[PDB]
Amino acid sequence: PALPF
Amino acid sequence: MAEELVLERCDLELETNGRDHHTADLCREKLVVRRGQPFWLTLHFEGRNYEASVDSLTFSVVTGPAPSQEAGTKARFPLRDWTATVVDQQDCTLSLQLTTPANAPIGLYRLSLEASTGYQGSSFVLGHFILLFNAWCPADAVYLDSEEERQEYVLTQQGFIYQGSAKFIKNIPWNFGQFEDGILDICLILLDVNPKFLKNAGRDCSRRSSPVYVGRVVSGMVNCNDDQGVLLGRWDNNYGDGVSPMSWIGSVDILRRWKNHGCQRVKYGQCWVFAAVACTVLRCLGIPTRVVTNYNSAHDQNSNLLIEYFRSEMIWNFHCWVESWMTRPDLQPGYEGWQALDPTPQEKSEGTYCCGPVPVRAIKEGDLSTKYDAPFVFAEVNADVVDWIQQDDGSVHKSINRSLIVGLKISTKSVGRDEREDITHTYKYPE
Ligand SMILES: [Ca+2]
Ligand SMILES: [Ca+2]
Image (cartoon, rainbow over all chains, first blue to last red; front, side):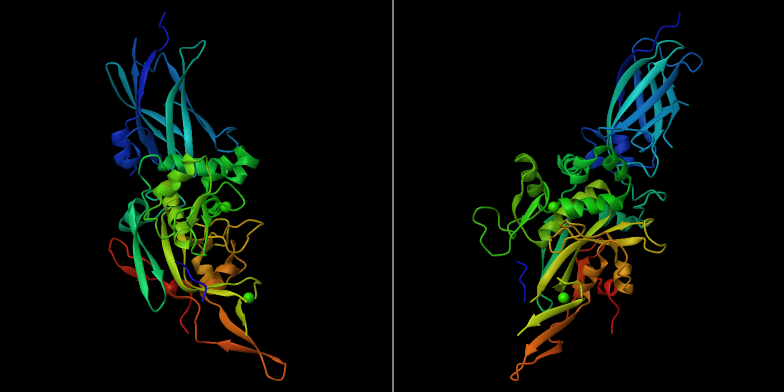
């Protein structure tokens, strides 16, 4: 998945 | 005495036209052609054949629900720029060659024939053809002068989409499947149910002559936000009432699921899914498109070109969008080529979750006044990371954070190879 740092 | 012409049937010449216009996979059932390029017809007659001395035939093409010559969605031309010319004549058949202008609106056209012998003209509906963008045609706006690149960016149905992180790069295969049965029809529906079509259908069809307009439309319509768009985004790892973003292997299941439930949002997608479905639709319509991945992708929320933490904006491991190849006569000269389009909702443009097209070159040069949405895309690829740190003395100090650099190892699939091309150079200068 796309993950916010 | 000479009685009127009687048509039996119009042969659309699917196999020949298909091979010539690079639409063979689209042409097994209905005629699909690319604009700005001749295509064949063959009229079969019942009584006598065409006679140039006797007969004068006139053609009519129309697209959309309000066709007009002013808009370029209706043309009339005589059998002798829309043209029709006689190429051969044999027994009962007459073989024609029609042409369309290279700036014609894409979409479904209805083709009629008027036949006269000097008196009351008789009318005939010959059939239907879908007209697409033509990357092979030098006069077309999407023209791409490299054959190997046209193969990759228009014709190839499989590709690779890059994910992961800057440190740990990975990829997945993806079936774009732009030429599978029913997908082109679903693309035309996507344009037909778009907000601007609902508002003013005649003007919307007229403007499908531009890949810019179409490109912008798609970057809006691929997400379900604000409209009857395709995908609903979700990012919290609970997808039990839909499909996991990571389940998908191709655009086709999504587009078909959207159509089958009456243009209803498809649960669920994330960035690469949006970009991937957009690539399908744009490739299907003939606009050369590719999926690009950007590592350490920044979300600027206040347009100050800074990504701000408080010890708050977001940097993603990766984000995906698409680039499409086209000239930009709506801009200053020199901006033809790749245009960033972004169908994933993040920031609103003109009151709606869309983004682009913006020239990649404008991003690189920092010409951020260039439309569309250059300030946002610049920040995604080339922003400074700032910490507003609160100090022991109650003061708040601004500091530049260089531990995580925004916009790294920007990637798309190599032309004709199963390998990764780095295109970081097109977005930003090295330092
Ligand atoms: Ca939308
Ligand atoms: Ca900011």
